[PDB]
Image 1: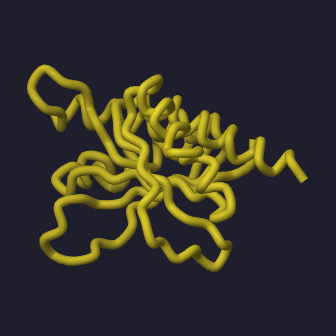
Image 2: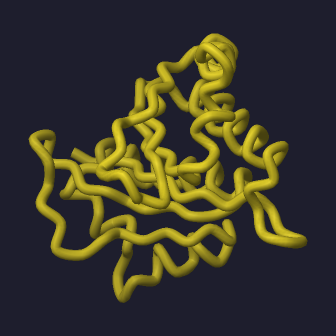
Length: 162
């Protein structure tokens, strides 16, 4: 139950609703979830998505991400007859990324089949100063939470070993 950083991407048009008047909503979410929730600066004036940085343990991530998913649903940011679907980025050790993929890509293939979330480890990544790379997770709230949960397990199982 360590403190993780998750980048959750939301539609740019929803920033005002997520922040709220005088920032009352995003402050409320931060207290409710017990997590830090900040809106990262925009890469440009016409980007279609904005990045929310959520810092906190798994139980806090569930509440912070969940309340953001739920707020977007209230604001009607889903497709017709569909659930709110968001992309999130998590950081895993570069040395464990191959284990998330599995031999022949079979581990990531089963993972996507069980959760219904799309799980992508972008190619040709340069590990960051912590020697960590990105895993992309796209799906509805519960699918995203389950995918995140199992990826965290794989990461911890590899550490356990040696």
